[PDB]
Each structure stands twice: as structure tokens, then as C-alpha cells.
Length: 194
Length: 194
Image (cartoon, rainbow over all chains, first blue to last red; front, top):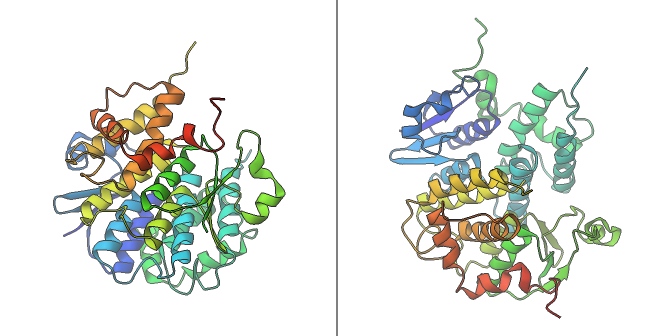
């Protein structure tokens, strides 16, 4: 019985929710309101000593970090694979992951940090033929791109026309249930329509 | 005939040099002076369009990003393995990698960003019994910790006594040839003794 400590608006938790949905894995969604500071609660700290969200609990095992959680899921529950067979395409997926993870993540506001990272991702992925980031199946890069692009568009009003490959990728996720289900607005702790 | 575009003081390139040495892989060291701005040279840009260092050239294939390069090497040349068999220990290695990659990396100066990241790494690794970060063999976390600790000590004069697990790890690398050989001061472009 997996548990996922998640916050509806966290892009890192969004990545993990896609992975769980693509693996067909059921889990208990445990909301952690990051705006309200619920991650500094001492009982939560008891269960999740690292203190970060997302956090996956798999029995006695607690995994933090979106990338480490996703790799643990892919290695424990291999089907469908989140990495391709081709060593070069696997390297592109890891590079795309790292630009998002460590490149970008960390009147009107102009966000050119995104410009910079999206330019690199476009540079990296434009030569990968296919429906999604690296081919016609969904892989690790796609789980990193979807939440990043959703956040760029919804929080920074970034225009995606300068990044046609990225735009293709993001449009390609609109019909995939695993991706639709994992969206921030669909989560149990998301702001209501009621 | 592998090629590695490297800069002697780059901690990211330091990580990759350890991996190449542990895999017993020969390569052409191509210096890229990052202080002098050699990475913005147009011919280098032709070979390495992504423009970053380190960059591994494996024939026609150019891989950027320290983590993606190291994974490509581990997957193409599996021996000795840079990840353990145990799924949980593999997850710890990826978490340690991510704290360094995306947590830390990006009168006297006091560097408490390091304090923060080293505190998390200590928290993460203290329950892993063994000579090195996650056991008695060298894995991915160790390739990320060595350059980070070398840089903390040599550029920021960080005292390692508050992080006994990390200190153990770093002392454990002093006798390993792969680690000694990859040090910044030993590289072809490093400042001279002459």
C-alpha cells in the first residue's frame, strides 16, 4: 500500500503522480499544504525525516526527491518502461531531466530563467523524431517536461511558440489519461469548483 | 576513442573523471578554460552545440550533463557497477546525487548553502552502514560527494566535523586511485608546480 505525500501545486509532486498513473499503481494521496507550512509539522517529520515533498512511502521505505522516486518506481515496477532501450536516447532523457531538475526549477514579471532552460531543452530535443520528447512512447523526459511547461504557462504566462518541439510535446500529453489525471487542478487538495 | 571536454577546477567534470577512471576507460582530455571563456568559442560550439562542460564525445555521440554522462558510461560499460543491486540503496544513491546536482551546486564569506545541503546529505547517509556512502563499494553517490566535498574544503574552507558520515566518506576516497587521479590539481590543464 503505497502512500504519496503530495501538494497539488508542487511541480515535483506532479512529476511523480504521472509516473504512478503510467505504472497503474494505486496509492494513498496524503496532502501536505506547502503554503501553510505543513511540511514543518513534527509528526510529518517523524514519518518523513528528510522533510521534503514529494515523499513516497513504500512500507518502511521512504523515498524523497522526484527523480529518485520515479527511478525507484521504474526499477521496482518495470512496466511500461520509463526509459528507452537505446543508450543514446536514454542519455537524452537523463539530460532533459537534469535541465529541469537542476537547470530551471531552483507591471509584469518577466521570467527569463525559463527562457534559458526552455531554449536548452528545445536544442536538446529537436533532433529526436517522434510524438513525445524522445520517440513515440512516453519516457522520463516527458514526466519532467509536462509539469515544467504547465507551470510556465499557468504561473508565468510563457508563450510556447518559440519552442516548437516543446509545444509538440506538451500538446501530445493532452489526450493521455495518466497525464490528465496527474494535473494539479485534479488533485484531492486542489482548489474547488464548489 | 572517447573524448572528454573538461576544465580542471569544474566539480561537474571532476565527477565524470572519477567515473572514467573507475571504469578503466582511456580518453582524450580536451581542456576548456571556463574562466577565460573558451566554452563560447564557435568551433567548440560546432562540436558541442549544447555548449556545456563536461561533455563526452563517443564517436558521433555527444553527451552533456555530469549525471547523464555518468549514467551513459555505467550503462555502456557496466563493470564495476556504479549502482548497487538493492532498490532502496539505489534510491539513496539517486537522492544523494540530486541533493548535490540540484540542491547545492547552483572579512570572510560564510557559505551556509553548503551547510544546508551537507546537513541533508548527512541525514540521508548516516543510516547506510559501510566504508563509503552506501556500503563497502563505490557507487554513484560517492562520485557526487567527492567533488562537492573537495570544493567545499578547498574553496570555502568548510569544516567537516559536523558531518561525520560525510567526513568518513571523504577520508575513504584518499587511498582510491580512481579518485586521486581525477582530482582537479592532477589534470593536464591544472596550475603548475613548475
